[PDB]
Image (cartoon, rainbow, N blue to C red):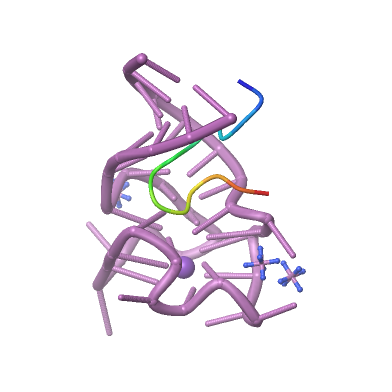
Length: 14
RNA sequence: GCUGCGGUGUGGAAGGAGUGGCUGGGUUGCGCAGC
Ligand code: IRI
Ligand code: IRI
Ligand code: IRI
Ligand SMILES: [K+]
């Protein structure tokens, strides 16, 4: 899971 | 690789899903969960 580790709205970027 | 829950806070009890996010923690951190 090399991608978004946290979702829902705008959580999890960088 | 994608997605969901203001669920977390060195403010988190007057808030939210960033319609404050070049105003910070934080290039949306942390936790939990699902495909
Ligand atoms: N969960 Ir309380 N954050 N710890 N609301 N009880 N203060
Ligand atoms: N400038 Ir800033 N926005 N505060 N360090 N990049 N995070
Ligand atoms: N501007 Ir900012 N919000 N502080 N993107 N660098 N993290
Ligand atoms: K805040």
